[PDB]
Amino acid sequence: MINPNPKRSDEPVFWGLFGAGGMWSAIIAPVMILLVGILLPLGLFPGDALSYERVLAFAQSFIGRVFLFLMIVLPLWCGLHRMHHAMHDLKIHVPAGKWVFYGLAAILTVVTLIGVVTI
Amino acid sequence: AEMKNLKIEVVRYNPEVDTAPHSAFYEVPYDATTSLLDALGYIKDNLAPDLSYRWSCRMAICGSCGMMVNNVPKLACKTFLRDYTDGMKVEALANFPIERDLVVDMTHFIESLEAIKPYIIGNSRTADQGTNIQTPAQMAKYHQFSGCINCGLCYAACPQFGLNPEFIGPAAITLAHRYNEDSRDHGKKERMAQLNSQNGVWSCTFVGYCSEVCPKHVDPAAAIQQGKVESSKDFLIATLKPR
Amino acid sequence: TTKRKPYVRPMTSTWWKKLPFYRFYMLREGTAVPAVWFSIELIFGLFALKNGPEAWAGFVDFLQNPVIVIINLITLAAALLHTKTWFELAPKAANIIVKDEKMGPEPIIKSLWAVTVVATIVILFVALYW
Amino acid sequence: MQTFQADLAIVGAGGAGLRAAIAAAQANPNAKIALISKVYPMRSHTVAAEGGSAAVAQDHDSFEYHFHDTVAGGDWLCEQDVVDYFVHHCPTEMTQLELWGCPWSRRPDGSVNVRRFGGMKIERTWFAADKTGFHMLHTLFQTSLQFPQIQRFDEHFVLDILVDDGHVRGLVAMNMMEGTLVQIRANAVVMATGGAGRVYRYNTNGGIVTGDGMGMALSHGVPLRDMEFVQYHPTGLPGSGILMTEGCRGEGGILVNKNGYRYLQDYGMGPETPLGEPKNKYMELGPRDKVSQAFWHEWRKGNTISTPRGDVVYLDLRHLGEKKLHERLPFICELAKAYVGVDPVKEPIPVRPTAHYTMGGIETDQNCETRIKGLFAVGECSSVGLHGANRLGSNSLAELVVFGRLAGEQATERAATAGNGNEAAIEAQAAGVEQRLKDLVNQDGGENWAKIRDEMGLAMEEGCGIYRTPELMQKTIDKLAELQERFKRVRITDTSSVFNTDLLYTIELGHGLNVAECMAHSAMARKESRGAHQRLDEGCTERDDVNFLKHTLAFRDADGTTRLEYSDVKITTLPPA
Ligand SMILES: *Cc1cc2c(cc1C)nc1c(=O)[nH]c(=O)nc-1n2C[C@H](O)[C@H](O)[C@H](O)COP(=O)(O)OP(=O)(O)OC[C@H]1O[C@@H](n2cnc3c(N)ncnc32)[C@H](O)[C@@H]1O
Ligand SMILES: CCCCCCCCCCCCOCCOCCOCCOCCOCCOCCOCCOCCO
Ligand SMILES: C[C@H](c1ccc(Cl)cc1)c1cc([N+](=O)[O-])cc([N+](=O)[O-])c1O
Ligand SMILES: O=C([O-])CC(=O)C(=O)O
Ligand code: SF4
Ligand code: F3S
Ligand code: FES
C-alpha cells in the first residue's frame, strides 16, 4: 500500500541551505536593495560614500569579500530551491530539474567565488 | 412562525448510474441554529432518501463529518446555514476519491496514519509499578498535537497532497510528531523512516492551509516544520555515523 | 464485480488561481524571482567593480535606467513581502515551553523584526556615514 | 457469502471493543481476531466522553469506599460480587492506559491528578482535560495498531450472529462500501456495541448508538436486563441535547430560573452555597436525580425560560473567570458558543435534562458471558450488573477497560475449548440472515422510516422520562406496538449498493423499536421507584426492597412479544438497609 521501507530523501541538504539562505535574505536583503538599487543610482548618499573608489576599497577588504559572497550566494540557494518547487506546484515538466536549478546555483556560486578571490 | 428557506446545492454521485458527479438542489428550512448536518438530515428525510453521508457526534468531536462547503473543507455539523444566505454548494471532501454522494474513500488516510506507528514504543514500565511521571511542562510538548480527531479536512486543504497522493499527510505526520515528543515514548527511530521519505515531511511546502482549517486547532503545519528540523538532524547524524 | 465507480476529480495547473489563500501562497513563493535577479545584478556590479571605474560607471548607468529602477523597486517590495512572511513561518519550527505552556510565535516574530531593524540601521550607517 | 476464519470476532471498536481486542492479542499471540465496526474505530461514541474515568488513586481512599459508592448509587441493584472485581481492577487499567500513552492531566510533581464526579466523597476520577473519552478511545485505537492479530473490518455492519445448539458460531455483516454480505466464523463473539440512547427524541448520544448489539441478542433468546433504568443528564443544550459536562458546576457554575433564583435550594439541596465555594452534595452539586427533577418542578411552577428550542433553565458560569474556564472548560465553551451562540464568560448557557446513559443491557455473568455459550457482551451494551438502577459518574469509561480486558481474555479461552459445530446448520443460519435481509429490501408499503423514528423518540421521551405514570407509560407501550406494525409497512426506496445508509438506518430503527419495548415494558412492570426509575402513582413512589430488590429480565419471543422474568441480586458485604 504505502511502501514499508521508503528511500530516505536527500532534501535536508537543499532545505538546509535554503534555510540559511532565506534567513540571510530576510534580515539583510531589504537594506541592500535599498543601498544598491535605489540610493546608489539616485545619488541619495552622503559625499563619496558609494563611489567607485570606496566600494572597491570595501569589496577588496576581507570582510567585504566574505559579505559580498554570502550576500550573493545564500539568496541564490534559497531562491532557486523555491523556483525548483514552483515548477512542480505549477505542473511544469522540467528535465533534470534538480540538476538544472541546483546546478545553476553551484555554477553561479563558483563564478561568485572567483569574483571575490578577485578579479 | 415562519422559517426562511435556503436553496442548497449538493453534488450527488451514484457509481451505479452516474458517469460523473452532478449537482442537485434542495429547499431547506432554517434558522439561526440550523447546521449543515441538520440540513443533510432534513433532505434525507423528506426530499431525497438516497442521499448518503457520514456523521455521528453532531458536536465536532468524532470527525466523520468532513466535506466541502463552497470549496472550503469543513465539518458539516459545525457549519451553519445562517452564514450562507447568498448560496451554498456542498461537495465530497476534496483530494479523496468520491465513492458515493458525500462519502469518500478514507483508506489512504488510515494507512498513512497506521504507517507511522502511533503508539508508545519501547517503555518497559508495567501496570504494577504505577504510571509514568510526566510533568505539565513535558506534556505541553505534544499536547496540542494530540487533539486530532482524524477528520481529514487538512488533507482536503493541502495542495501538495492533491498533487502527490502518496504524501503521508499533515495529520499523519502530526500524529507521529505527537509520539516523538511524548517523554514516555522511545520509538522515534521506528518512525523516522517514514518522516524522512520524499512522501514524508519533505513533500510539504508549508502552504499552511491545513492548520487554517483544523477544527481542533492542532496546527499540523507547525508539527511538520518541527518534523523537518528533526528529519534534518537525523540526516546529519546518519552522515556522521559511518559506524 | 463491484458496482462502485470511484470518481477522481482532476487537479489543473491553475488550482492556486481559485482561493485567495493559495494565490497568496503563490505570491509568497513568487518572491524567489526578484530575489535571484537581484543576486545576478550583484554579480554584474561585482565584476564591473573589478573591470575598473570605466565599467563600474556603466553599471551605475544601468541601474539608472529607470525601467531597471522600477524593477528594483518591485524587487524591494518582493523582498519585504518575503521578510514579512518568512518571519511569520520561521517560529513554527521551534517547540518551546515556557512554564507549562507552548509559547510563540509572537515573541519570536518580534525578535526577528527587531534584529532586522538594527541590521538595516547598522548597514545604512556603515554604508553612508563613513 | 465469502467467509473468514477467526478465533474471536469482536463486534464494536469503542472503548470496550478495542480493550477487548488488545487483551485477546496479548493473551494468544497467534490468534486471528476480527474486530468489526460500522464506523472507523475513532468515531465510536467513547470519543465524546468529557468527565473522566474512576480509579482509586489517593492514599486516603479505599476500594471499599469506591465499592460502597457504586452500590449506594445503584440503589442496591448491583451484583455486589461484580462491583468488587470492578473497583479492584480499575487502578490497573487506568495506569495501563497511561503506559499506552493516554495523556491524563497531571499534578505539578508529574503524578496524575484526579477530580470529583458522580458525587463521590473522595475524588478518584482520572481525566484528560475535558476530552477524556477522546483521549482513551484514541489511545486504545492507536495502541491496537501494533497487534497484527487484530484484523479490522472497518465500516462493516453486523446484521446478525450465528447460533446453533446453544453456541455461537460467528456472524454475518455487510461490507458497507461494497454492499456485500460476509460471513465471519468464530467460536466466540464479543458484543461491545454500546447503549441505546438514540431511542429518545433528545439525547447526548451519537447517531450510531442505536442499540443494534442489544437488538441482536434479543433475537436469539438472550434477555436484556434492567432496561427500565435510563440515566438522564441534568445539563444538556436544548434541541441538540448536547452534553454540558458536570464540570461546569464543579467549577462553580450555577443553575438559575427565569427569576435568576438558584431554585435547587427549595428542593432539599440547600442551604445556598456562596458563588465562590461550591460544595459536593449541595445545590448545583446535589444528587443527579434531584437536580433533574428540580427542573421538572420548576417547569410546573412556570419558572423555566421559554426559548425557540424549548423550555430551559440557565447554567451560569461567568463568575468562573477566563483562566479557569479555558484551563478546565475549553470544550464546553466552544460547544456553547457554536450551538447556542453563547460565551460562558459573557452570558449564561440555556440547558435542560437529557437522555444520556443506558444502564440496562444484554444479560451477562461475572465474566461477561451470556446464556448463549461463546457469546459475550461488555460495555454499555451489556449488564455485568455493575450500575444497578443508577450508574455512578465516571464509572462507565472505567468499565470499558476493566471489563473489556476481562471479556477479551475469557472469550479467548472460550474459543480454544469450543470444539466444532454442525456446518450445514451454521451455513443454514447465514442463508437465513441473507434471506431476511432480502425480505426487508423487497418490503413495500409507502411508510417513511424517519417519521417512525421521530414518533418512537417522542414516545420514549413522554412515557419513559424522569417521572413516570402508568397512564403515560402505557400510552408509550401502545405507541411502540403501533410503530412495530408500521415498521413492516416501510419501503426502502434506495436500492443502491455502495454505502446505502437508507437501508442501514432502517435496520438500526428496527433494533430500536425492539429495545424500546423492553425498556417501556420493564418500567411499566416495576411498580416501585428506584434510582433512575421514578413513578408518581400511589404505592410506587418509594423504593420497595421487599418485592422489587430484583433485576428485570426482558425477553422477546418469536411472536414479537416482550416477556419479563426476574432474578435476584447478589449481596456480599453490604445488605440493603
Ligand atoms: C454519550 C456520552 C456518554 C458518556 C459521556 C459523555 C457522553 C456525551 N461521558 C462519560 C464520562 O465522562 N465518564 C464515563 O464514565 N462515562 C461516560 N459516558 C458513558 C460511556 O462513555 C459510554 O457508555 C461508553 O463509551 C460506551 O462505549 P462502548 O465501548 O460500549 O461503545 P461505543 O463507544 O458506544 O461504540 C460502539 C461500537 O460498536 C459498533 N457497532 C454498533 N452497531 C454495530 C453494528 N450493527 N455492526 C458493526 N458494528 C457496530 C460501533 O461502530 C462502535 O465501534
Ligand atoms: C559545476 C556544476 C556542477 C553542478 C553541481 C550540481 C549539484 C547539484 C546537485 C543536485 C544533485 C541531485 O540529485 C539528482 C538525482 O536524482 C535523484 C534524487 O535522490 C537523491 C540521489 O542522490 C543524489 C545524486 O546526485 C549527487 C551530486 O554529486 C555532486 C556533483 O559533483 C560534480 C562535480 O563536477 C566537477 C567535474 O568536472
Ligand atoms: C519551516 C521551514 C523553515 C526553513 C528554514 C528556516 Cl531558516 C526556518 C524554517 C520552512 C519555512 C517556509 N516558509 O515559507 O517560511 C517554507 C518551507 N518550505 O518547504 O517551503 C519550510 O520548510
Ligand atoms: O457527563 C459527565 O461529565 C459525567 C457523567 O455523569 C458521566 O460519566 O457520563
Ligand atoms: S489535523 Fe486537524 S484536519 Fe487534520 S485530521 Fe486532524 S483534526 Fe482534522
Ligand atoms: S497545507 Fe500541505 S504543504 Fe505542508 S503546511 Fe499543510 S501539509
Ligand atoms: S458528527 Fe462528529 S465531526 Fe460532525
Image (tube, coloured by chain):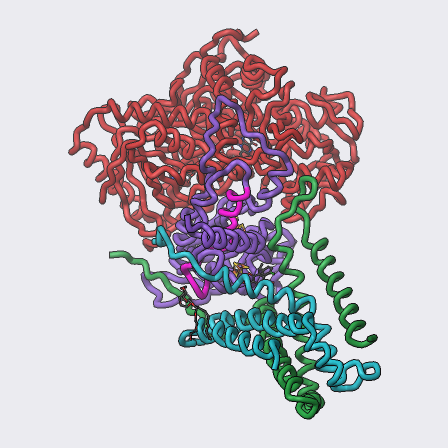
Chain colours: A cyan, B purple, C green, D red
Going by the image, does D41 lie left or right of A50?
left
Q: Main secondary structure of the magenta part?
A: helix
Percent position of residue C100, x then y: 67, 40
- Residue D103: image quadrant is top right
> Front-most of B119 and D130?
B119
Percent position of residue D421, x then y: 19, 28
Figure check: D443 above or below B23: above
Q: How many marks?
A: 0
Percent position of residue D44, x then y: 46, 40
Residue B40 visible in rendering = no
User: For the magenta stretch, what is the residue range?
Assistant: B161-181
> Front-most of D336 and B29?
D336
C33 in magenta: no
> Front-most of D190 and D256?
D190
Q: Residue at the location (51% across, 27% down)? A: D94
Percent position of residue D372, x then y: 30, 24
Q: Residue at the location (61% across, 24% down)? A: D118
Figure check: A94 above or below D204: below
B162 in magenta: yes
Residue D559 visible in rendering = yes
Going by the image, does D350 lie left or right of D198?
right
Q: Residue at the location (42% across, 69% down)? A: C10
Going by the image, does D103 lie left or right of D490?
right
Figure check: C39 above or below D26: below
- Residue D485: image quadrant is top left
Q: Residue at the location (61% across, 62% down)? A: B84
